[PDB]
Length: 73
Image 1 (cartoon, helix red, strand yellow):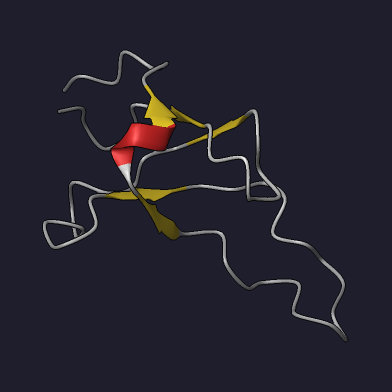
Image 2 (cartoon, one colour; image 1 turned 90 degrees about the vertical axis):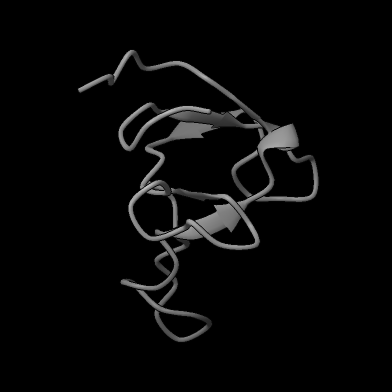
């Protein structure tokens, strides 16, 4: 497994972040049932539909995530 900072690439298909990366803020709190909480710079800032400070941290399934950042402490 990776680390907390080890920027993984979101390869879902059914997502607004398809072909994008983010920061894996997982292996701190997401020692549970779904493994990987990642960062998103595009959380859809349309304030009267969703919000401007909504879902930046979201939990994935690793099958749809490949490693990019050598963030080993």
